[PDB]
Length: 208
Ligand code: SF4
Image (spheres, rainbow, N blue to C red):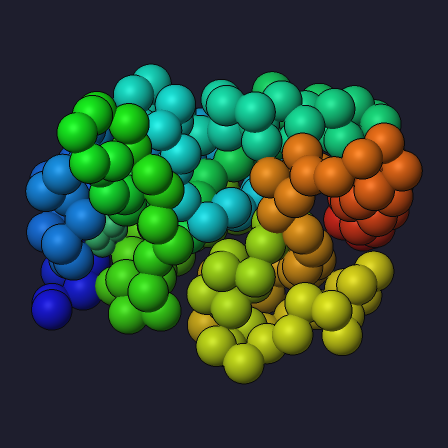
């Protein structure tokens, strides 16, 4: 039950931070995961985006947003004229949490508890201290609550620029849906979910 804090080194070097996250024992999730999935991008990024946790594909690659949700994220970024390669993209929890299907190898993603999110939050703080983003997009409720408190309501602040204490640099925060949700439902449901995410990404990119 320790939390990640005493496993986080005092450095802004992202490769050093990523290796240290591989050695983190701040919660139980390191055990069955393949590896840490640290954030991806350069310190030169001025927009950071934060999801929930790895999926199966992310866990195998050691990279964020490489599966189907990442594909739809990329499509929405393109619609918002945002270059993904200029971003820093990461997740609130850095080890894949899952159960195995009975009788097989298939891994079923399971959502981190609030305790696991808080345990892993010091890595987000180190990432923000390193990258110094102007704006942070919180992709989904888990990432939003990680910075804005466990009773934060994404539905009550769509399109709003937020700020909160204990976030390095006091960046603009924009809380939106997680891109996995854009995979759901028939044509018009997907198209409305897409539009809503694009609107929020544009708010974030237009912060000046
Ligand atoms: S999930 Fe986060 S806190 Fe838990 S072990 Fe992995 S890095 Fe450490």
